[PDB]
Amino acid sequence: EAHIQMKAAALKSAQSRLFGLDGGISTQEENTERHTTEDVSPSMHTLLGVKNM
Amino acid sequence: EAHIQMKAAALKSAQSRLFGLDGGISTQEENTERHTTEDVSPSMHTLLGVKNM
């Protein structure tokens, strides 16, 4: 009885977690898009439908 | 768990780029046109259909 009470008092209410933080860090997608000197910006190739006035 | 958290905090949301700026710089076409003493301008040969009055 003493050993059981000691074990119960030591363990308390320790929740058991089956997993931790996943090791897969990359949550985005690889950017396979090309970059060329013809681009108007590092994020865009052309401004196709844009109309100035 | 500590190592996984450290790796996740260090990598953050680093997007992976597959390409950089392309090494092909010349985006125009080579000007194979000739230049002759008969030309009226370095950019034009004659003024053919032009009518003065």
Image (tube, coloured by chain):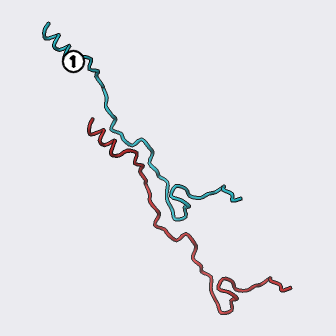
Chain colours: A cyan, B red
Seen at 17% across and 14% down, the residue is A7
Left or right of A10 on screen, residue B47: right
Q: What is the number of callouts on the image?
A: 1
Residue at 46% x, 66% y is: B23
Residue A18 sits above or below residue A48 on the image: above
Q: Secondary structure at mark 1?
A: helix
Q: Residue at x 69, y 83 (%)?
A: B44
Which one is nearer the viewer's eye here, B18 or B3? B3
Image quadrant in which you'd find residue B36: bottom right
Which residue in the protein does label 1 denote?
Answer: A11
Percent coordinates x, y for residue B14 in the rendering: 40, 48
| Residue B27 percent coordinates (x, y) | 55, 69
Seen in the image, is A53 located left or right of residue B8? right
Quadrant location of the C terminus of chain B?
bottom right
Report the quarter where the N terminus of chain B lies. Answer: top left
On screen, residue B10 versus residue A39, left or right, reads left
A51 sits left or right of A44 in the view: right
Q: Residues within 10 Å of mark 1 (few under 14, many from 20)?
A: few
Q: Residue placed farthest to the right in the image?
A: B53
Q: Is residue A6 above or below residue A35?
A: above
Residue B16, x across and y down, in percent: 41, 50
Q: From this view, report whether residue B7 is shown above or below residue B21.
A: above
For residue A38, what is the image quadrant? bottom right
Amino acid type of the residue tagged 1 in the rendering: Leu
> What residue occupies the far top of the structure in this picture?
A1
Return the chain for callout 1. Answer: A
**Can you give x and y, in whole percent of width and height, for residue B43 in the image?**
66, 82
